[PDB]
Length: 53
Length: 53
Figure 1 (spheres, rainbow over the protein chains, first blue to last red):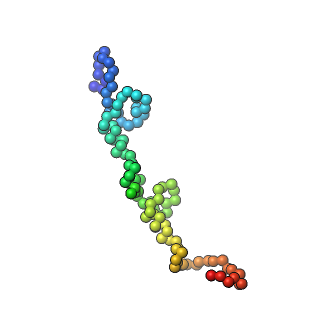
Figure 2: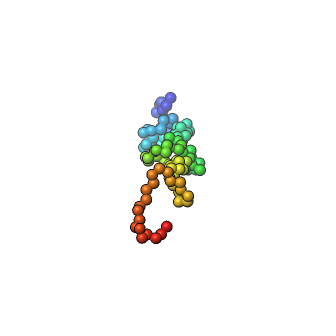
Figure 3: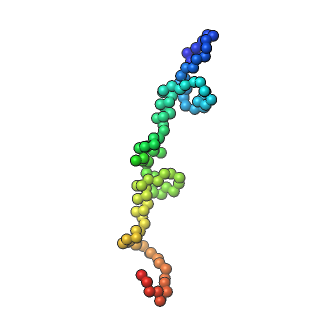
């Protein structure tokens, strides 16, 4: 379900891995929109940022 | 207009200071114009021949 099967060319597929160490050195795997969104939700903006903690 | 939760007036660490915190801290100090000193204020005893303000 994640990579497929058979003797077919390894075309890239968007991975839905959580943000972390698996995100370095990929060079041919694109992220998923959920994966990007989850990390971006936890970042401060340049303008009108409401810092907490 | 970036904002952050105001730290306590006793905070003396690397936490970001807010304008409300600054006002709260300065509320305990005397201004140049018409200060009302309370308690036991002390000043330097000048010479008897001193002739200024």
